[PDB]
């Protein structure tokens, strides 16, 4: 079975919109989304379909760009740093589950370097 996906809304959690968060959706996510290596990260890992039955035995804080995108569209975050942490969790989980040089890891590393370039400068 797959676990329930991470929440994309939470009425207990305060919402906010900042220039930097609009930018993380408008520019950073929506450009990463178009990368040729983006597709494995556009939705939660379906460990049933991919025959990775050990995935959620190892990965306990799963994160993906589909969840991030919905969070950004919902103004789920308080600030840009909260969103950047979700990106880092997504990359870090892929390096934890897989090994250096794996095809998926090369994909994650391409996106990560592009992500780092894009958030080097955020709007004021
Ligand atoms: N062994 C794998 C396979 C993945 N995948 C998913 C679709 N096609 C390959 C995968 C995807 C991720 F977003 C993170 C990972 O850690 C992954 N690990």
Image (cartoon, rainbow, N blue to C red):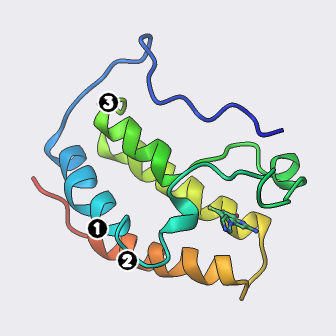
- In the picture of the structure, the residue carrying the numbered disc 2 is 114
Q: Secondary structure at mark 1?
A: helix
Please tell me in which quadrant of the rendered image residue 54 appears.
bottom right
C-alpha separation, residue under disc 1 versus residue under disc 3: 19 Å
Instruction: Give me the residue at 39% from left, 75% from top.
Output: 35
C-alpha separation, residue under disc 2 versus residue under disc 1: 9 Å
Q: Secondary structure at mark 3?
A: loop
Q: Residue furthest top?
A: 12
Task: Find out whether the residues at labels 2 and 1 contact each other: C-beta distance under 8 Å.
Answer: yes
- In the picture of the structure, the residue carrying the numbered disc 3 is 74
Could you tell me residue 108's position as x and y percent?
A: 56, 74
Q: Secondary structure at mark 2?
A: helix
Could you tell me residue 56's position as x and y percent?
A: 81, 47
Please tell me in which quadrant of the rendered image residue 109 appears.
bottom right
Q: Left of 100 or right of it: where is 89?
A: left
Q: Left of 69 or right of it: where is 75?
A: left
Which corner quadrant holds the N terminus? top right
């Amino acid at each position: 079975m797959n676990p329930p996906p991470p929440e994309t809304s939470n009425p207990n959690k305060p919402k906010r919109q900042t220039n930097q968060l609009q930018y993380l959706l408008r520019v950073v996510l929506k450009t990463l989304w178009k990368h040729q290596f983006a597709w494995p990260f556009q939705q939660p890992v379906d460990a049933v379909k991919l025959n990775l039955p050990d995935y959620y035995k190892i990965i306990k804080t799963p994160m993906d760009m589909g969840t991030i995108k919905k969070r950004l569209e919902n103004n789920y975050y308080w600030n840009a740093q909260e969103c950047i942490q979700d990106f880092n969790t997504m990359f870090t989980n892929c390096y934890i589950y897989n090994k250096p040089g794996d095809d998926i890891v090369l994909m994650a590393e391409a996106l990560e370097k592009l992500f780092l370039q894009k958030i080097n400068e955020l709007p004021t």
